[PDB]
Length: 47
Length: 49
Image (cartoon, rainbow over all chains, first blue to last red; front, side, top):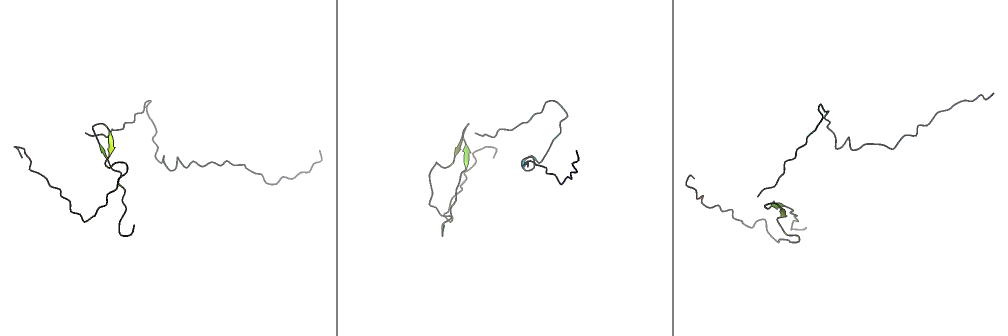
């Protein structure tokens, strides 16, 4: 009971986490306003 | 590569439905940049023209 304890600093134990993809390829965002979302792609092929 | 340059060409032309390479799989062409080539165009055989 008669402890008389001091406390020093504490650690954090952080992750090894860095996106590198939402910062290098996905630089642009687009919030929605509707339910469905379309994405067209024109085909290139000629006679 | 000394006096001769090295050039790689992977161009493609599209057939009716398939895409095929201009040059075959393994060929090379000993050529000259100063070789004269003709781009002759004929006469347009159209009455309106």
